[PDB]
Image 1 (cartoon, chains in turn yellow, brown, purple, green):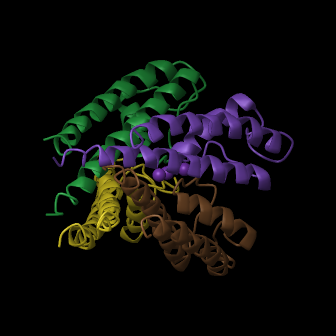
Image 2 (image 1 turned 30 degrees about the horizontal axis):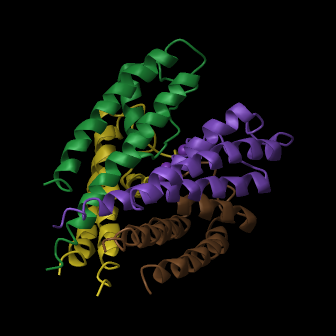
Length: 97
Length: 97
Length: 97
Length: 97
Ligand SMILES: [K+]
Ligand SMILES: [K+]
Ligand SMILES: [K+]
């Protein structure tokens, strides 16, 4: 189909974004007055919180670039998740018959 | 129906996730350099904030596992709530006649 | 209509929740080891952040009850806003002709 | 069309809100007991976090007005993003034929 397949697949996109932003924000903060976004195994848990947009505050970028990577990893979530909602929004309309 | 019943019921699923993650993240952090996620009556209020994805920051996991439980209790919310939006999105289309 | 009127009106409901939770969480925290949720003009800005679910962390309840009021003022937002999305989701389908 | 064009365009609205709230919250906090919302290049990253509603906590307004600008820059996001979800919700229904 699409509405049901454009989603199940997109997520496989967000996950890339995560791992992508993770091992990129680090190399953007690793050397500077910034928080623990100086470790790959740390950026991960950050990508996730950011992507889910929960913002624990426990971690965040301070590097101009690191902040960019944040924005990206953000929409990725607001978006990657939106589709899943879209998918469901129609699969509830697919019961109009 | 479905669109209107697949929701009212799913929530009864998220609530399980809460209580589920609550009394699981604790036993994952209870003994370690981590925050108050060392008390069941505390993990709760955390499951909720996390699930609603508000991330007060007042509490969060530091245990690799405790972080997993977080992720889970997270989607549960982004999702459990999405349906409710889906439900409503169609119940507004159910006025096309 | 509905999809377009059930929303514009619901918000007038959330706003009540705000002012409602505001001047209720205070009288729940006002006298205790809790944060500034001890002032009505402060609970407001909290209801808002909470309702929008942004969780600055700058403020939060510590009173068991105050935490309840939080939950409420939370869904109110996840929900009150969901409808508005629902409304829009259909007003985009109302262009199928 | 609309559902697909009312979105791609709205965002160009939120971005204005950002830059708009950015260089406005500052001049509202710049001179007071408030956080770094005293620098334009700082308010930005705040508008974004706020707009995405992630609330890192790293920054927030304390000025009554600065708090207003927050609210605004908030809905702008909850809303500007909602449409995009709406758009997608229908573009999944546009496969009912
Ligand atoms: K959020
Ligand atoms: K948040
Ligand atoms: K926070």
